[PDB]
Image: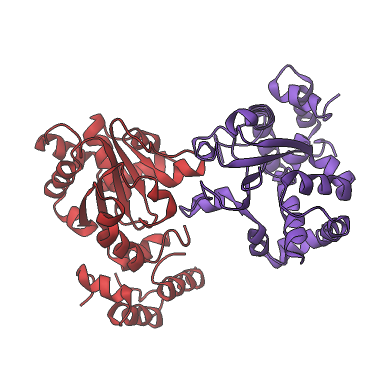
Chain colours: A purple, B red
Amino acid sequence: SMNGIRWIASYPKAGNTWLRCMLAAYITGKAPQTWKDMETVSLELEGMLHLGDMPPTEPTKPVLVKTHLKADVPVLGLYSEATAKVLYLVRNPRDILLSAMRDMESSRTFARDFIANEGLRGGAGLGSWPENVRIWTESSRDRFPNADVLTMRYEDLKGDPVARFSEIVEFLDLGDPVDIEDIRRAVAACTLERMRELEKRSQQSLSFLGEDIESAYQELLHGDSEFAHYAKQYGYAG
Amino acid sequence: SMNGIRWIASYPKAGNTWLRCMLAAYITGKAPQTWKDMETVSLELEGMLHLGDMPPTEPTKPVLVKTHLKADVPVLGLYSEATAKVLYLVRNPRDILLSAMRDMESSRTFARDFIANEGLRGGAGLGSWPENVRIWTESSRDRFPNADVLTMRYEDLKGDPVARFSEIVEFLDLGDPVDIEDIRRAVAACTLERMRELEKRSQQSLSFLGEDIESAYQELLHGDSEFAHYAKQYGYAG
């Protein structure tokens, strides 16, 4: 559709933020200097809800909302009809794990938790990694019957940002035709250093944790679990 | 009404929890041992929303929900028709301030913040103290046109728990007639020590901060501010 909700959905640390920076820069025309800047272009569902706020259930315009919640949580139900687009980002779960921790004893325990849970524990509306990936990539067209769905790997976005981001922008159908030079500008606006300034201005293998831990991950990764199923599917496992 | 939402609303630390313990014990028949126990009897709106969950917009039974959000936040709007009762607890703002901090430099700054904000900063859907008190005690019958409203001081509940809590239980209209002996049991189930075990098992004047700070509070308290208006109204000021 043209009017309606665009979900930028993903498991935490799956590239969501970086994308929100690029979307902010592409649309506003200027590179975000703080997080507030990004809020101009896209909302955080969890943030809104934290304040008893929520996105428009009947939107007169395109609306970009980020969330990490599973698509089946009761709140998302409210937007069954109003949702026009679903963008889902996937990232290598290992990279999510490492990312989340950022004191060996402290980390290992965390790492252990992650492996035992196949993800993060917010909590239950977040689901495990495979849970979140499955629901969004497979059940979205059910939960949002007016929506087009697009799934992308963080890694792929990262390897060809101009190509992939233009695809994303095009998919989102924001009303104007995509201009590639804007795309490049937007990619450049959210460089690693830039993302670093954002953090600042707003304030491998698992071997180091121990081979015992790498081992445990590898078992999960190649085992018979749902986690192992979706990892393999997105080229994160053998 | 009989079916529908019962809000247990208040500013944070205004007695809400203690009441939820008594309600849990009155209803289940046993003293809560953890917080999960209380969730049996009453829900936390913020908690649910945190998980993308939410209370029933069309409830087939009486439903007790706690919240600290202002009654006018967009999310509460969803329950305009379904709300049957509003219980609002008020507490002495000074006691809320002290309560919230629980390292002089650390506290003073906090205290200062509080005074400058007339309350807490979650954030904006929480509103300042006077904001929260005003909206709930005055605008409730507007926002929930099928609801009866009852406001009570934490202090009064504390001074005559059996009398006040029976009033509360009666007001809530949970379906069964109030039995006083149950009331006493429920009060006894949530003694100070008991409340202490709950914390554990689940894991004055502002002079000490400095006379400069007490002074600042006193100015707020007797000044011309909304804060000062509602304080005076509930007997917390001169």
- Furthest residue toward top: A224
Depth check: B224 or B54 in front?
B54
Residue A10 sits in which quadrant?
Answer: top right
Depth check: A151 or A90 in front?
A151
**What residue lies at 80% left-to-right and 62% top-to-bottom?**
A194
- Residue A171, visible in the rendered structure: yes
**What residue lies at 60% left-to-right and 32% top-to-bottom?**
A145
- Relative placement, left or right, of B8 versus A208 is left
> How many marks do you count on the picture?
0
**What residue lies at 38% left-to-right and 74% top-to-bottom?**
B208
Depth check: A149 or A93 in front?
A149
Residue B235 sits in which quadrant?
Answer: bottom left
Residue A211 image point, x, y percent: 81, 31
Which image quarter holds the C terminus of chain B? bottom left
- Relative placement, left or right, of B6 versus B125 is left
Q: Is residue A201 above or below residue A102?
A: below
**What residue lies at 86% left-to-right and 24% top-to-bottom?**
A238
Which image quarter holds the N terminus of chain B? top left
Residue B84 image point, x, y percent: 25, 43
Depth check: B49 or B222 in front?
B49
Residue B56 image point, x, y percent: 38, 36
Residue B141 image point, x, y percent: 25, 55
- Residue A209, visible in the rendered structure: no
